[PDB]
Image (cartoon, rainbow, N blue to C red):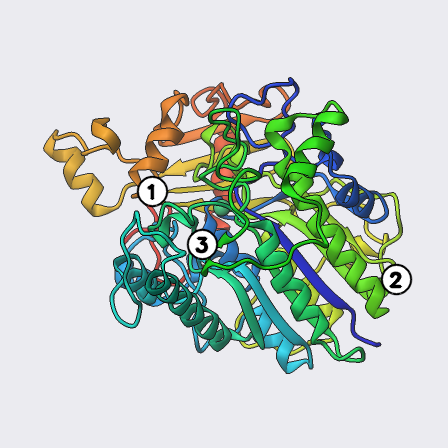
């Protein structure tokens, strides 16, 4: 009654950048409210129109684990004290953040804090931020997990049992980090299941898990639901093969992250009907997966209404980071920029917009304020958005944004972006040796990628001539596509931006970075 419910709905690798042509040529599309004219997302568009659209939402680290970490903590990913992260980055060494950060079992996170405030907390979908040591055991199918062949048939009773068993372990482990419920979970991505048949997205499976959570909330108790999609992450649902979409709408709805099960999803359209509707509206059939999702969000809104809690629920729709033009795990705009809308009938006026710089670190301090939490242990980097949400604040709430990905750090203002890349000791030694780096599919390279992941580095560098430039300065008014390095043309401005970067770097104890902070 006094505390609003929060439903946080997150897609995976979905830029806000619209694709202004009928064939998207291997790119994701954003929602209709982001300006894509080729999609059909009416429920989500109406939620956005009847709430607040943020046109300059960013993430501090544009790669899955790091973005998710920040979302659920309010802190920069470079502050993680996760077990794997600290083994890679002992005190006194620079950090190289990628998919290697996790929630710490004895530190604050949003879910733990909301539980202390009296919220029932629920988790559905993709994690990527819990127990990376256990993730390694999942990938290798080591105890406590059970093993199966990559080509195994999940209808096979012994195989189905193994995959179900592995899914139950993650449900239990996720609830050690502040959740009262966890179901429809993925430890990481579809890849890490190592099974061809279940290497498919399943909107319905996770949606039913979400609705089951909402059903079990007592009507007078506040709740928080973290609803984390796999879509449209690789293998992308839009991939057309033999006239079909085998990773999305034409996959078997019986295959899911827990194996095989014939569940009743008749409260959603059939997958065929989804495709039929998009084709009838002369919208892009490759991206019918967005309408598939729209209906799932529609079922959530229907359930909230039926329970009489819709008007006092804050629904957030966003993505963890972009992947436009292979700019995932870079500090270019196709990684940083994400869709963001917020809908809350009793707290946000409709037809609202905010164009100031906001960041994923802002979600936790915002929700904490709405939940009446005033005492936290771990310092928060983000800012509460509640004055923006209430329509009181129409100015910028910060002078600049900070970013970090692997060997790269960056800052941006409204009009300028600065990126610095500085090498770890191991990379620097290979560079000194004159030997090339062993690359993805034999694409060896002279200089390090920002990240250790050679697949991401290969794709991020392939059509980006400036990728390896150690100092990059872009004017966002004369060069929105970031094709012209002004570092040597505007040295005074570069120095001004370096000051802003240093102000953020010095807040990470025992973390050097090139000549900014010496080892
Ligand atoms: Mg992602």
Q: Nearer the viewer, mark 1 or mark 3?
A: 3
* Closer to us: 407 or 452: 452
- Residue of label 3: 65
- Percent position of residue 278, x then y: 71, 30
Horizontally, residue 457 falls left or right of residue 33, namely left
Instruction: Check the picture and name the quadrant holding the C terminus.
Output: bottom left
SS state under label 2: loop
Q: Is residue 207 above or below residue 58?
A: below
Q: Residues within 10 Å of mark 3 (few under 14, many from 20)?
A: many
Decide if residue 446 is in sight here.
no
- Percent position of residue 188, x then y: 42, 55
- Percent position of residue 240, x then y: 51, 27
SS state under label 3: helix
Residue at 40% x, 23% y is 466
Residue 280 disc label: none
- Residue of label 2: 346
* Closer to us: 111 or 494: 111
Residue pushed farthest front?
A: 156
Instruction: Tell me the CA gap for discs 1 and 3.
Output: 13 Å
Q: Which badge, 2 or 1, comes first in the chain's sequence?
A: 2
Instruction: Tell me the CA gap for discs 3 and 2.
Output: 33 Å
Residue at mark 1: C-beta within 8 A of ligand 1:
no
Q: Nearer the viewer, mark 2 or mark 1?
A: 2
Q: Quadrant of residue 130?
A: bottom left
- Residue of label 1: 451
Q: Which badge, 1 or 3, comes first in the chain's sequence?
A: 3
* Closer to us: 443 or 461: 443
């Amino acid at each position: 009654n006094k505390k609003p419910n929060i439903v946080f709905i997150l897609t995976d690798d979905q830029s806000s950048i619209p694709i202004n042509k009928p064939h998207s040529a291997g790119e994701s599309r954003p929602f209709g409210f982001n300006g894509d004219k080729y999609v059909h997302t009416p429920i989500i568009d109406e939620l956005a129109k009847n709430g607040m659209i943020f046109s300059n939402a960013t993430v501090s680290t544009p790669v899955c684990s790091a973005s998710r970490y920040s979302i659920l903590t309010g802190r920069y990913a470079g502050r993680s004290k996760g077990s794997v992260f600290m083994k890679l980055h002992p005190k006194g060494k620079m950090t190289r953040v990628e998919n290697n950060v996790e929630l710490e079992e004895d530190q604050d996170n949003l879910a733990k804090l909301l539980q202390k405030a009296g919220y029932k907390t629920g988790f559905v979908g993709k994690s990527h931020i819990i127990d990376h040591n256990l993730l390694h055991k999942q990938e290798k199918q080591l105890p406590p997990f059970k093993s199966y062949d990559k080509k195994a048939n999940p209808k096979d009773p012994e195989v189905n049992k193994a995959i179900h068993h592995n899914h139950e372990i993650w449900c239990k482990r996720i609830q050690d980090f502040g959740f009262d419920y966890a179901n429809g979970v993925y430890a990481a991505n579809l890849r890490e299941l190592f099974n061809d048949s279940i290497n498919v997205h399943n909107v319905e499976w996770k949606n039913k898990a979400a609705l089951d959570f909402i059903d079990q909330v007592d009507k007078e108790e506040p709740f928080f639901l973290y609803y984390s999609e796999t879509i449209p992450h690789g293998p992308a649902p839009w991939i057309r093969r033999g006239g079909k979409y085998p990773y999305g709408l034409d996959s078997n709805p019986s295959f899911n992250g827990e194996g095989y099960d014939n569940n009743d999803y008749s409260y959603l359209p059939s997958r065929d009907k989804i495709k039929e509707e998009v084709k009838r509206l002369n919208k892009d059939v490759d991206h019918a997966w967005l309408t598939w999702f729209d209906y799932a969000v529609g079922a959530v809104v229907k359930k909230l209404k039926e329970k009489g809690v819709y008007e006092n629920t804050l629904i957030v729709i966003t993505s963890d980071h972009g992947n436009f033009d292979y700019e995932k795990a870079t500090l270019y705009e196709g990684g940083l920029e994400v869709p963001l809308a917020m809908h809350w009938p009793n707290g946000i006026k409709p037809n609202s917009t905010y164009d100031g710089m906001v960041q994923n670190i802002d979600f936790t301090p915002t929700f904490l304020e709405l939940a009446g939490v005033t005492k936290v242990k771990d310092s928060i980097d983000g800012l509460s958005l509640t004055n923006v949400l209430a329509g009181k604040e129409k100015k910028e709430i910060r002078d600049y944004l900070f970013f970090e990905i692997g060997l790269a750090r960056g800052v941006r203002t409204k009009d300028w972006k600065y990126i610095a890349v500085r090498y770890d000791e191991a990379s620097q030694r290979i560079v000194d040796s004159g030997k090339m780096f062993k690359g993805y599919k034999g694409h060896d390279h002279k200089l390090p990628h920002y990240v250790r992941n050679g697949h991401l580095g290969y794709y991020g560098a392939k059509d980006h001539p400036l990728y390896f430039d150690k100092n990059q300065l872009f004017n966002r008014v004369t060069d929105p596509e970031e094709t012209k390095n002004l570092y040597n043309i505007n040295s005074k401005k570069a120095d001004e931006m370096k000051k802003k970067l240093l102000e953020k770097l010095v807040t990470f104890p025992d973390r050097p970075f090139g000549e900014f902070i010496n080892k």
